[PDB]
Length: 129
Ligand SMILES: [Cl-]
Ligand SMILES: [Mn+2]
Ligand SMILES: [Mn+2]
Image (cartoon, rainbow, N blue to C red; front, side, top):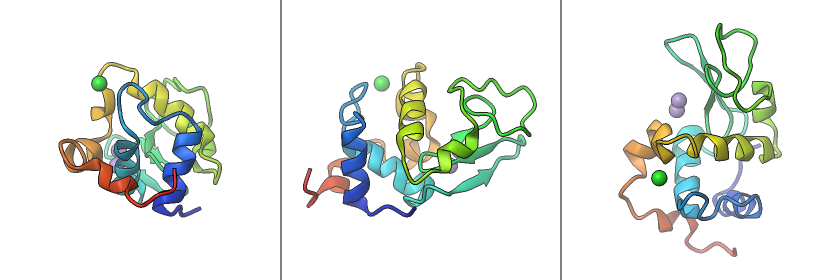
């Protein structure tokens, strides 16, 4: 599923991401925009042989099992394919673990490089929330 901006904002709010670990909703929308272009089916292979999955591009070395990443830790205890669903619940639940891991949202390279320090409230402007 390719989400609209306000549609995703609303879904992320329903799932408890607004101000989760101090990160306002706009941060999460911005991260999703630049990680996946709001597409739940996005996948991208990394140089280390791992793959990133879904709307928040969650990595198979640490967080999910894709059956082809040796030494995967699977810390979210899910198949990576579950992160490609039109229902964002699994992605959100796993993202909550990731952002709690010590480095906050810096775990998402696109967030650090494209969202951090910007007017992230713009990403939810105009939305009925
Ligand atoms: Cl933080
Ligand atoms: Mn990425
Ligand atoms: Mn990545």
